[PDB]
Image (tube, rainbow, N blue to C red; front, side, top):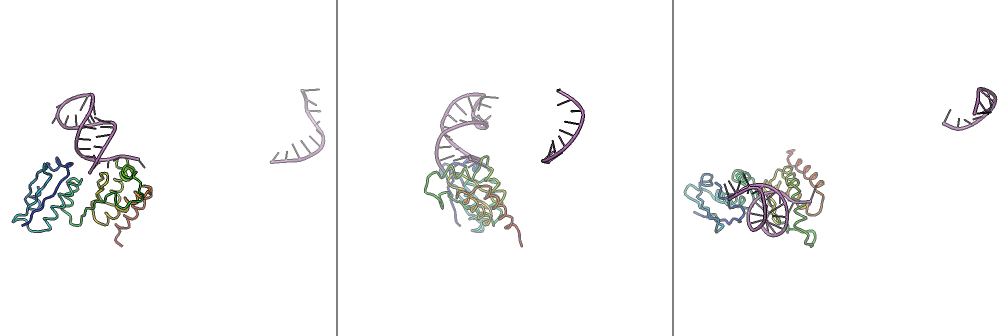
Length: 175
RNA sequence: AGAGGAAGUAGGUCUCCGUAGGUGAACCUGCGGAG
């Protein structure tokens, strides 16, 4: 018998107050969004450390900016990963014109560039300033990560999107 | 002004917060900030 408690940011508290993991994995839950904690407890119907760690990963992935439409995908498919890239990781210049210009390049007006990158490499990303979070299979996470870091190296989004599309097609192909 | 003669050229998304107005709890728009 093991328990795991996770902290949540003060962003998604109403969305966590929305309504089930006891039905999903037979693992008893408690919540308190004023101490920012969510208790996960394993019962006699709870069988595996896989179920424990996957419930923990599902709740933390809902906490870090994804909704349930992209979180029950993590509850369901075991090939699905999350990777959280800080924009402060590997940096091309020392100059502090970073945050606004970089996430203006990555996000794009009305979400055009983030959305086209998502549709191109089949991954699902969310963007909040310094931290950008990628969800999907880890080769798609590698594709989205190399596209985003080539966006912050200062390459144009048209050329980056073209190369991303051709790499995504060659990765979809079997032989 | 005249019929002839002869010639030549052809780039801030999402979420939250503080605002100000709107039709009020909520909610919408605009702005200023943090993730």
